Figure 1 (tube, protein in one colour):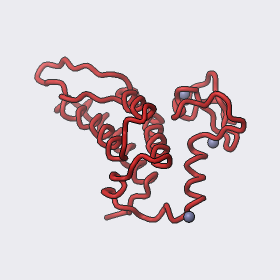
Figure 2 (cartoon, protein in one colour):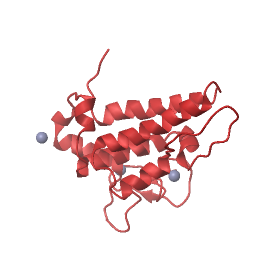
Figure 3 (spheres, protein in one colour):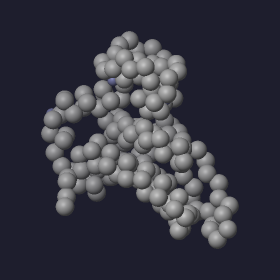
Figure 4 (spheres, helix red, strand yellow):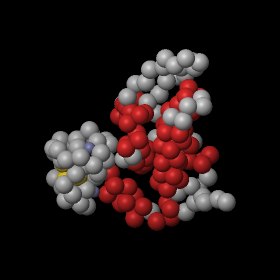
Length: 178
Ligand SMILES: [Zn+2]
Ligand SMILES: [Zn+2]
Ligand SMILES: [Zn+2]
């Protein structure tokens, strides 16, 4: 196995995948690393199995159809993995915990949102369709853009949204366009 967490790139108390070389902190893996299960297979491994079981699942899809999918186990897993891909970027720190808003000339968002809130909402099965999860994720970045206005810090929202959107297109096999 690797000697650092795949998500945060730090050492520590690492749980090791049995089917690939990755390792994880317990609360860095999504879902949190399971109590028993020997062998244990990480989310990367579980996503690759889905693809291998149904190769046609990589054919292009329309985003509108993806969003309307119910959160059955395979879509639940895909959202977990997309969330994890965002935490993989170090810039996710800015969006992880509950924000607060007190800047001259701006007003906070009507509906604050943050990664750990989305993580809880997935864990508690609060989303019934893919659209629920994607809306809350895009809301994080939209709130940041609107609040920070012309401050150059707005760019952090653009950057981490780009990571989200590239991974969304990959994981859900969105049809490539010009
Ligand atoms: Zn970690
Ligand atoms: Zn693995
Ligand atoms: Zn098949």
